Figure 1 (tube, chains in turn green, yellow):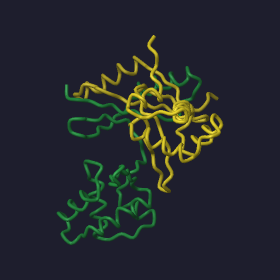
Figure 2 (cartoon, one colour):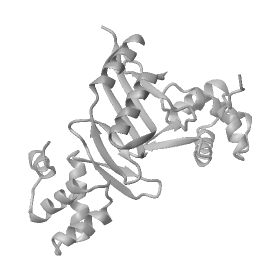
Figure 3 (cartoon, chains in turn orange, blue):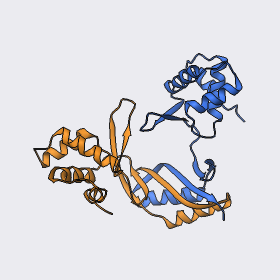
Figure 4 (tube, chains in turn yellow, green):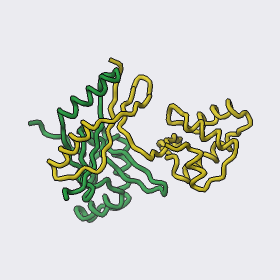
Length: 133
Length: 137
């Protein structure tokens, strides 16, 4: 549960007023943003930030393994934070929003299933996709 | 029971001109244990039909990709691995020691997932569950 700027500072990255704005925009993003969204939001905060600065800062965060790049066939990219703690997710498809949840009850069933098949469960990923009732 | 549709049959259905060499490559792709790269597809295909060239394997793979039968995963260094697109969906248990995918279904887990969805005000329309296992100690 550390901020993006903290992670950056810890991993040997030079920080500044503009790079911290970018980090916050990127931390606060509802979506998985591209560089165009990151720039548009950052210039609302600091009108002096250039598109070159946004791009440069994003690349450095990627270098540090704080964010992961997802490339599309056409060469455009979207970014996600690389999580320290991994949770099950319930996706609100209508709003494109993620809801964190935990279910020790399901986890115990998963352990039983794994065991019946010859395995000790060491990790899991569960995503649920929902529409309003 | 229905006759399962093979990768080469799907390729044909999607307008791809199949040749014996392309069928060999289709079968190698469908039967691959891992998510293969072009190198592995070539090494395995040439053991079936010694006349198959690397150029042919590459060309054929791109055509399967064009047909939406396989999807490509690119790495930072430009290398790629491929996976078939599933009509089989399921939940999966991964044997980490071997890379084996074990399919399973759990009505009990499904009931709890629906309940979690419901309690957050949602109807569940889909789910993805991956379990990661090591051999029992």
